[PDB]
Amino acid sequence: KTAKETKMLMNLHKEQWQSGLKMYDYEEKEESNLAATKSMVKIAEQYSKRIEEEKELTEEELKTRYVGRQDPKKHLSETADETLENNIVSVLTAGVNSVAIK
Amino acid sequence: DDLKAQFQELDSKKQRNNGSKDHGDGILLIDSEIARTYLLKNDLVKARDLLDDLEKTLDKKDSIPLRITNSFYSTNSQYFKFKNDFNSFYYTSLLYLSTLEPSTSITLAERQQLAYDLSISALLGDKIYNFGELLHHPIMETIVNDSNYDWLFQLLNALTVGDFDKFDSLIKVQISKIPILAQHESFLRQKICLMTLIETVFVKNIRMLSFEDISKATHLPKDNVEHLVMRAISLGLLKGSIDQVNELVTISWVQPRIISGDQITKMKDRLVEWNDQVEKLGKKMEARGQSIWV
Amino acid sequence: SLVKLFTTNELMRWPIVQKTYEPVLNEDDLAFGGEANKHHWEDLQKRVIEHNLRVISEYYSRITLLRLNELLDLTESQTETYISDLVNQGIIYAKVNRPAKIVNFEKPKNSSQLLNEWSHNVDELLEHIETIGHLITKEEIMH
Amino acid sequence: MVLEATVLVIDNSEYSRNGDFPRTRFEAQIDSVEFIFQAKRNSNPENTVGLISGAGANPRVLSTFTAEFGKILAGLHDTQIEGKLHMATALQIAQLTLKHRQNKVQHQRIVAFVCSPISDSRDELIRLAKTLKKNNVAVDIINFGEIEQNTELLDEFIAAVNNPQEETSHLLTVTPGPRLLYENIASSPIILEEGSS
Amino acid sequence: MSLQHEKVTIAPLVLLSALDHYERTQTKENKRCVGVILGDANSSTIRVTNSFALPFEEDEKNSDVWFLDHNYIENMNEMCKKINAKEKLIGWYHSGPKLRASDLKINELFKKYTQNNPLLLIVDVKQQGVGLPTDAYVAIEQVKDDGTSTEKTFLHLPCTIEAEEAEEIGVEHLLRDVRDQAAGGLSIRLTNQLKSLKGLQSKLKDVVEYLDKVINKELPINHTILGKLQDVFNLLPNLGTPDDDEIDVENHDRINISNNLQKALTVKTND
């Protein structure tokens, strides 16, 4: 391969310059934040159940015997990080726009 | 009618001899002229549906010579002034000028008579504030020393500066003379007042104006002021809202106008300033949290 | 001449519109017409003022109550009945003050409205700059 | 003449709807486009002819070098009778069409019809005259438009351009009056020309 | 002919290919190549499947003079359809680097073949920008009054791309990169944002110098453009407005949610 060919394949988004200054309409952000918090209240209840146990001999045996899968731990960690990054970008974008343009 | 039959027959053979030539052009011209006969004999009803049909077939065409569309607009122009509809004629006249044949068969008399109808339309008009632009074109541009085109053009230029005083003197004499102006008195009287309002508003780019500014410029009582503010808004010339409790007009939108030379520089000055802002902001923020940019 | 009046937003006071088209349209039958027909004609009044109010909400964001009465050509008590009827019907948004202060038609100004409008504006800006850019390219070739 | 690719320029100016050649000047030319293809073929059947227009602002490639009669004919049907002759554009484009060919062994000939006076700038013509020599092209002009009242700008150029060689560029002046253009082309040299070598 | 051109998606193969063709004909030193672009259209979505070179000669002296062999395009094409009916003649590619008014003459010839308005695909081979060096333009014919009577003009349409599944596995197989145009994870999107700023800065500069040339080298005043810049300034945000206060309040909610999410995660790590 040549580095002329490589560069062409590599760029695949002419609307990069736009889309990163583009921020989502704001009615959707509010909606989302409530959903995310409230949903985690319910996966916290399930978290509590999980750590009632944590006593069976052998971690692996716990997962089979009382069906430890359907793991609340993993859903709360996933959710929290997903929502976290979203909010980092949101605060950054809006704040950047405000000063650059005015 | 003799020529119309003649051509239809001829083209049948002739299309095949050329092997290609659009002959549906000739027909349209014939058709156009017949509608014109009717207007002269004052049969506006027959002439009307023939204008309709003409406009549809022409525009279905993806390519049209100048001659054909010019003939059709001529027919229209005449129909609108006969009827004494100022608004419609102005729309036509413009078009006719754009598409106007490079032929000089078009007599000076024809030019002079149209020039006259266009200026009368634009007094009476519904959206014309483009009076200067109009004057810059051959049709009026050259025909200025003549007496008919003196006081006439004086009016247009009185509108531009919004002088109320010059306006008043001209109009008193001329309202008798031209009878179109007598019956359309309301329009004409509103028109000077409006043109002043658009001038005051454009220069003060601040977002609020008291009623007192309008009162003095247009020299009207306050009752009349808020109505005049309703009219601009209805035209779409302006957008905003009216506070009666504080006696304000909050203008929130200005309608673009002719960009003069001075303004080219003004634009440039602000754009440099806003270049720098983007520039300052990107450089510092690269430096901040340099470590991660995967 | 009748339809074209009511479509344009330039308000017009009842007493006169009455007069104007009375010797014209009352002549014709259905809706207007004779004696029984006059008790259907009547409604046209009501139409005129809920058109006027409607225009006023758009243009006037703030207007005094005494003034609004003057425009509508109605005593204080009828004016206020009618404003009430329009908000129930949802045609307009209204806040009235009876000690004869202000009647405000302005949009209740929420959080959402400020932000969402701002959101739009910003995309439109970006869109403009781009467009300008295509056309500078063109002008080099012309020139 | 032997194994030859030809760009024929058929011109359909505003002067071509005339009737100098009865009944109609256009129809006398139609027959000539057909005849030229045939004469060249009859010479040596490995000859080919392609077609470009003089008509319009610019030429249009209707047909490249081909042996099919059919392509010349469909192209021939395509005309505009209010076209106009520009000598310079037609020459230049013809040379380009010649650079690419079905068989590149074939010799390079331009046949061009002139059906209106020529008033193109002289400067343009001078330069083209010696371009042609670089790439070694010959050209025959079937002339009947120009002579009606306007002195020949091309003759001298072609003459100077020609060498001892089988190829022979020519100025052919053909009686412009009623006699049928095609008939006169058959009765004058066009494939009865002799070599210059 | 058709308005159906509202998005153009272009296979990674088309972009790749055009670039290769440029050097396999050996047209360089500011010499154009025109080739036929084959693929699907007659749809809002245009999908350029493939491309092929066309013999081309460029002459700088007159731009009224050019070679394109007409008959070649048509023969080559019809064989391509039998493999795949998907390909139709949908237009022609141009090697750039810029839009021309000399692109219009070429345009007319190809419009005879086509049943849609030819797509004019500018693959710029100077490979400039952080975005694609590919602009998309469809010839629109519109009636317009500005002294001119009817304008024919080339209007920008946005560029996006689309890739077939097989072609996509092939693209990653070449690259050792995990890609960064992805708009993937949190790292990648911060990166793109910084790119977006540097991008803007350049575009604005170019506007500044256009204005300069009009007031110093007397390019004729073109009203239309300035009209638009006028609005850009009229719809400009402004400080001191209670608008700003709202955004500030909004900001407070968003830090509240981050604060809670981060603390939830302190628990998770402790666990």
Image: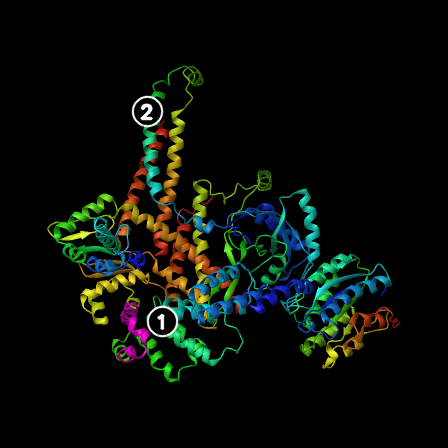
The residue segment tinted magenta is B171-200
Q: Position of residue B115 (x, y in %)?
A: 41, 76
**Category of crowding for the residue at label 2, using alpha-carbon neighbours closer than 10 angstroms: few (below 14), some (14–19), many (at least 20):** few
Residue E107 falls inside the magenta stretch: no
Measuring 32% from the left and 41% from the top, which residue is drawn there?
E254
Picture quadrant of residue B249 = bottom left
Residue E133, image x, y percentages: 54, 54
Task: Please indicate, yes or no, whether residue B291 appears anywhere in the rendered image.
Answer: no
Where is A80 relative to E192, above or below? above
Give the structural element (helix, strand or loop) at label 2: helix
Label disc, if present, on residue B122 of the rendered structure: 1
Magenta-drawn stretch, dominant element (helix, strand or loop)? helix
SS for callout 1? helix
Categorize mark 1 by other alpha carbons within 10 Å: few (<14), some (14-19), many (20+).
many
Horizontal side of residue B130 vs D128, given as left or right: left
Q: Which quarter of the picture shows residue E85?
A: top right
Q: For residue B244, what is the image quadrant?
A: bottom left
Mark 2 belongs to which subunit? Answer: A
Q: Which residue is mark 2?
A: A45
Query: In the depicted view, which residue is nearer to us: D53 or B258?
Result: D53
Q: Position of residue D146 (x, y in %)?
A: 73, 77
Looking at the image, residue C65 lies above or below residue B174: above
Structural distance between the alpha carbons of marks 1 and 2: 77 Å
